[PDB]
Image (cartoon, coloured by chain):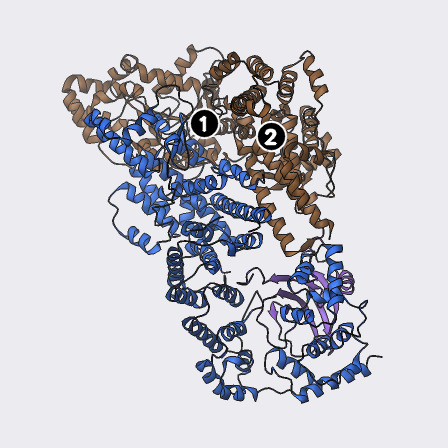
Chain colours: A blue, B brown, C purple
Amino acid sequence: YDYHFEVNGTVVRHKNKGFGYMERFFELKESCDERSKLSKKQYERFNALFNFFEKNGVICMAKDAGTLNTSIEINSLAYHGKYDVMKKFIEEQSVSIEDDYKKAFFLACLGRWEESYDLYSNIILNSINGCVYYLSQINRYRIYQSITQAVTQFNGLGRHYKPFTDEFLARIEREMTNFNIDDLFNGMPFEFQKKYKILEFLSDNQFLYDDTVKLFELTNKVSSDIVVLLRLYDNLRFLYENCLWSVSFHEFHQYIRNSMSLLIEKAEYERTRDIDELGFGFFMEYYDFVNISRHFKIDDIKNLERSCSIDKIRFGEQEKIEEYLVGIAEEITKQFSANGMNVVFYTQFISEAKAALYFAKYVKLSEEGLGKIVKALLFYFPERDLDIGKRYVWLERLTKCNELPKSIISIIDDFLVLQAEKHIDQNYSEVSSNGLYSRDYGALIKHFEKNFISKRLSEITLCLTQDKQKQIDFLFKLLPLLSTNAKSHLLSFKSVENINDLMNGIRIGLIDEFTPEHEELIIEYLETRKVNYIDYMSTFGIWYFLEEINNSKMEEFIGMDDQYDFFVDPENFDYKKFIPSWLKNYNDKLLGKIAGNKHMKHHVIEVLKERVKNSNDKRYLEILMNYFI
Amino acid sequence: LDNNVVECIKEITESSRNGKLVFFVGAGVSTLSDYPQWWRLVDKYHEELYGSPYSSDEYLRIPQIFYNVKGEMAFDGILKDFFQVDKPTNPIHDKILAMNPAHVITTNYDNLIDTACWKRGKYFSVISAEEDVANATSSRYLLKVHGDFRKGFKGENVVLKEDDYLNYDQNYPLISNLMKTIIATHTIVFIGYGLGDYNINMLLNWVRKLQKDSFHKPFFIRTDPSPIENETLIYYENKGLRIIDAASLIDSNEYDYLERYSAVMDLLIESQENKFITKDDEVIDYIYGKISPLFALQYIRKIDLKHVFEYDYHFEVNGTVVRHKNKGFGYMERFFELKESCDERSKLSKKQYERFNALFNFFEKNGVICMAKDAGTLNTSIEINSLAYHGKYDVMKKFIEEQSVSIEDDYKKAFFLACLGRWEESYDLYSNIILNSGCVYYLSQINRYRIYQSITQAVTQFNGLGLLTFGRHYKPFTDEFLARIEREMTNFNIDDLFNGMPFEFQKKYKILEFLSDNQFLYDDTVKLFELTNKVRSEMSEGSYSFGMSSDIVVLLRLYDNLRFLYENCLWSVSFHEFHQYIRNSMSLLIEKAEYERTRFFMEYYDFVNISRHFKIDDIKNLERS
Amino acid sequence: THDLVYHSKINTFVWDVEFDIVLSDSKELNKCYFVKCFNPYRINGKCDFAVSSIDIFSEGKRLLIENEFNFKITKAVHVATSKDVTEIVLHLSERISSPFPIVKEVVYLDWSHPQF
């Protein structure tokens, strides 16, 4: 505690009442003339000290601080996701026992926890300064904890996997029985406990409590941000460059989550406060992107997106981020295109890959890198993590910064043809957690092209027969992608006899323009309902108001459904019957059309104003503010 | 097993947990690893001295005769050709290591224990020669009292011949002294000895010279094929030994020594996690042993109770207990069963009844109700019984004016002086309490360091900005006081205060370790950030939950801290980080209440929390939102 | 009704319950629930008006609605606590006045959209 060493690399005299040896060292460093005064041994010792201090980012004292450059740079293959290089390093013959420590960490980061445990045990055998020995003991306890937790989770969880043989589990349970991580440091040689006191925190259950409690400075509303970010970078560099497995634990991931989330929230708060006062901050780089991808869950990224305006956060080092994402895509392909699936590695890697591809929305990607990422996401991402709807969401997010090129459209077309091929089987049905299916990919393609015709799906449709029903009702949702001949061939497999067939045809996109016979069918259903008076009524009213129906013989059925009367003739509607919740069921197009009617606009404006005043409902408020309905 | 055997197991396991267990390993453990026994060496010596092939004294005299006649060179040659072998380590070596002994004293001159320590990953300073005692690299020793062959397979490096044993005290003063000191200061378990060994009886003879009760009786793991005779057992237990017989525990063959050793060793290892609780009296005794030290403290955070029971249970802030990592008997469930059922209370013993009553009072006043599955409608009104929390400045002044009737009154007075800004008097009172005091001593040390930090920061502000802020350079503390407190606190280290404490304090008061740093706020900070994210995500999507609010934990934990820091008179109440924690908790609660209003009400405690821990800008932000 | 959540963006209730219902064609379904997906930025056609898309799942597999889905709930059962909650379901359905008032889970597709 003789000096503070600040995160920017400036030293400050703190608690030493003797000679200012740090100031003298810096004075020696700045000017070479007094360096010759040292002896030869003292000269080489000073050279080693200077190399250490410049490698650890210690430049000078605070009083002599000038243009301070604080750029994060982690020398770790594990941090950068260089899995192929890590595998090559493990394959090589380790010259030193320090190379074995790196090898054991790389094995841990690749999911090979049994090999990592064996290597750590071997290093402990061959390591009795004793600094690698203590670190190997720490990391072996950490990997034993990881193996135990993974075994528990695999017992709890979609297919029963046994990555660790029960003989290995029993062996490590017996080896690490009654093993005290707390007693480890105290049992070290008394010289180690003096020279390497700073390592004792690696034996603690928690080591980021201080860094987490200092995160409250980001919640103040009255630099702290730079201090927090540089402290996070310091922790990451220490835990990765020194190959410490606690970097993979939930405590460190939660700490990174909390720090990054609070930094982004604080920057957003400063931006809004400035806008309030000045009336018109956090700049993300490659390392921030990798930290968010590795340590954030998708729910955490969603909380970040709803809380703050990430689109207002500009992204730097986008070539580095694109290289990271392309490496993630390549590893996804290697893990799943081939039989290289490592379940232990998969569990940790799939969350990072998901988060990286989710956060890639804010990154401008080159056409080739976008092609690699899109192909890996569509084809080689396992369905247990990213189903059809989730994978569509991930893909469509990539169009925010990269409007769909022709190559990506071809990849999505290949995906669509593969999905159609999967529908040869009658048992196959797409499972979506988002309600988004293969029709949405074709909708996106037609949105970004408006003239794209997929030749292979047209060929599939022209080959279709009446037997394989699944293919027809699959390709009917992909109707705009087909050619004229394919459209004509497909349209022969469905009938529009009764009104239910008409509703099915509208819903699946079979027919987009209302023929007079469809209008007559609608009127027949309406007459039947009117006769039997003493779900589709609202739909027909909305279609009439949306100018989808120009039959003009619907006003006969005014007085049964309040929504139908509201939509057929807004001018004559009684608005005490209006239900505000109706506005919560309409989409952008319908709400905008209601806003521009010049009728019913003031009634629904008053309804929305009453709803906002009475309930402070955010949905009603945003409906009233966006379209001014 | 037998009651006294179970008591021996309990003592050994307690010593192993405390790091005060030392294993005295004899030739029997090495013999099970097929290391050459000494009778073969005596056979060879007789073969060279005489035609062809003893008493206890002969085992030493025949090698002595071989030495005196044939030469140290011949003795060296036979020792080298007999003992230069490689043998595997027993599972018993690994069991001894897994017991985590403080030291391993051994009469074995082999490296089998060394190889086991190296394989398992234990670092021991191997002391086999006189010069090794001063050159030991650690405080944990592998003490080979009879030497070994590390320097070489020479007869001078080991205690084998008769002359070696006669001159042992003269030739090994440091090693013998260290062995006797380890015996005096630790709990000793003898393994690998035959109860008639020369070393065992020499140690029992030395034990005779000691005072009547100045030493703890060493344990002796007897693994002879036949059960010990009763008269032999009385004779050796009256000599200072506590014998655990392997033959009495289990039945095995005469020559099957491995299972006899393994029975006792595995019974000791598997008992490390065992608490030996069957009856309700044992439940009450164990829970009382865990809880009674906390009777000194006014209040205990419920999240801290998981450390008291070593993560056996989750103690939720609503007062419900949950099984977390207790693989043994459920003593909390049994305690609550005794609490609900009045008839089973009478079944307890006389002492255990009062112990259970004390436990009931502690748990009821700490808001610990029952297990989660028995939870009903839980509602706990917050009440902080502190004059400092309520701002009773006149009452604190009057209480300070009074004469202290105890050291707890002095502790409260020092806290009240700190809260009234009389930091010099508070520091002096904390020093006086430290002089006269170990819960109160540790807490006064923490609070005196905190008040010294407060004085230092206040002096820095007054000298740097106080003159500008007040328009006048204020000097609340004289330079004499500042210099004196700097001299007293220049070398004080708050991080090592808990470590430099009696082991009984570091075990009974593990939860007080967190007060040295901001680690005591870590769990609540993490939970607050998590619940803030969850609540804000819920408000963003516009969802309303019918039932228990998601922020109740944030409230409860909040009042778990204020009650703990104020009723226990800890200066951490003034911490800037603690104020930020309270501010964030109250801000989240008010935001959630506003969200549910247009779909919590402000009380006296909430008003006081907002007044004390919020700046005006924080209140303005809440008023805006 | 302790895990019952009222989602107000689309005025529905998320409740972990199953429905046994009958349509207007006497067809019977058992242990069926609904999942709503709020998609304001969905790429609509000319005839799409709803802001949410709802999928019906019976016995863990979704249904293809080819007929009119006018239905009446005959028995609603809470999975976590097997207590019958039918009466509460009808009460909420009458109060809510929106299609499918009670839904197994609501998926919000707004925050994950590129246009969010």
Disc 1 on helix, strand or loop?
Answer: loop
Amino acid type, callout 1 = Gly
Q: Nearer the viewer, residue A19 or A261?
A: A19
Amino acid type, callout 2 = Tyr
Circle 2 packing at 10 Å, graded few (<14), some (14-19), many (20+), is some
Cβ–Cβ below 8 Å for labels 1 and 2? no
From the image, which quarter does the N terminus of chain C lie in?
Answer: bottom right
Q: Is residue A204 left or right of residue B511?
A: left
Circle 1 packing at 10 Å, graded few (<14), some (14-19), many (20+), is some
Q: Quadrant of residue B442?
A: top right
Horizontal and vertical percent for residue B586?
65, 39
Q: Is residue A514 left or right of residue A530?
A: left
Q: Is residue A372 left or right of residue A311?
A: left
Horizontal and vertical percent for residue A101?
32, 43
**Residue tagged 2:** B286
| Residue at 71%, 50% in the rendered image | B596
Residue B19 numbered mark, or none? 1
Q: Nearer the viewer, residue B280 or B75?
A: B280
